[PDB]
Image 1 (cartoon, protein in one colour):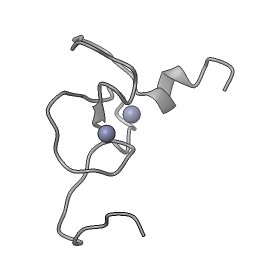
Image 2 (spheres, protein in one colour):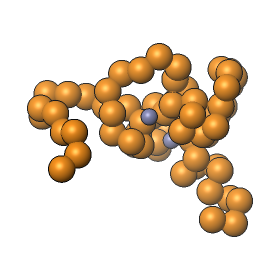
Image 3 (cartoon, protein in one colour):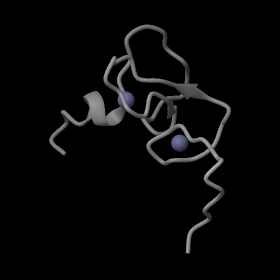
Length: 63
Ligand SMILES: [Zn+2]
Ligand SMILES: [Zn+2]
């Protein structure tokens, strides 16, 4: 089942997968995932400033 790896394999997105090309990270001092894919929020470019992940701001769109 699935495609697991060693306990020596660090991850990033809410997907729990390895390093990747295009990335942005949540701006909260309380985010417990801290990094995300562009496509895990629906981005196509890289903004700069306070940005929030989908469980942190996009959830306020009636489920
Ligand atoms: Zn991802
Ligand atoms: Zn976050």
